[PDB]
Every structure is written in structure tokens, then in C-alpha cells.
Amino acid sequence: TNLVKNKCVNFNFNGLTGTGVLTESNKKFLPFQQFGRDIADTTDAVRD
Amino acid sequence: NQKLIANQFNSAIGKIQDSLSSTPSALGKLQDVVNQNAQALNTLVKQL
């Protein structure tokens, strides 16, 4: 389904389920990298 | 000895500023409180 940004949304990405606001990320993600995680297991950043 | 006492008092006050600045551990007591709280909170988050 079409990506939605700047609004609370329930998101299932490649079998990963979470509810959070989606915003564009200025993170310099390395190409090999697919997920960015905080101290907690929850995924801070995701690649489409 | 009013004049003498006044000079002594003024001199002592002047040193106070220098003392706190030079001694990094001067405010260690206050700093400890901050660290302990932060430390505890990090642990809680890590446990998740």
C-alpha cells in the first residue's frame, strides 16, 4: 500500500509491525544497512 | 580595624570564584546525584 508520512500510522514493513509516525530521515544510512535500532529493540528507522 | 577586615573579606570572596573553577570535583556532590538518576534510567530502558 502507498506510503503515508507525517501521520500516525500502523506499518507492516517486510514482516515488521509497528505503529508510529513516519517522517523522512536525514540519517546517512549505509547501503548494506536495512534497519536502524535505538537502545531498545524497537526499530528507530526503516528502509522502504 | 574596619578597613583591614573589609579588605580581607573582599579578598576571600575573590578566591571563591577561582576555587570552584580550578577544582573540577568541587561540585562533585551535586553531579553525583545527576549521574545516579541517569544511570538508573538507562538500566531500565536496557532491560527491555
Image (tube, coloured by chain):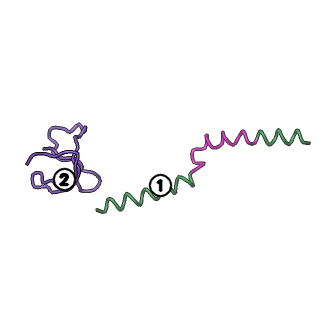
Chain colours: A purple, B green
Residue at 81% in and 41% down: B8
Q: Position of residue B16 (x, y in %)?
A: 69, 43
Instruction: Tell me which chain the residue with mark 2 is part of.
Output: A
Q: Position of residue B6 (x, y in %)?
A: 84, 41
Mark 1 residue element:
helix
Q: Nearer the viewer, residue A45 or A7?
A: A7
Residue at 13% in and 45% down: A3
- The amino acid on which the numbered mark 2 sits, given as a three-letter code, is Val
Q: Nearer the viewer, residue A7 or B41?
A: A7
Q: Which residues are magenta?
A: B12-27
Magenta region, main secondary structure: helix
Residue at 82% in and 38% down: B7
Residue at 49% in and 55% down: B34
- The amino acid on which the numbered mark 1 sits, given as a three-letter code, is Asn
- Residue at image mark 2: A9
Q: Is B21 within the magenta?
A: yes
Mark pair 2, 1: CA separation: 36 Å
- Relative to residue B14, is residue A13 drawn left or right? left
- Residue at image mark 1: B35
Q: Position of residue A15 (x, y in %)?
A: 10, 55
Mark 1 Cα within 10 Å, few/some/many (few <14, many 20+)?
few
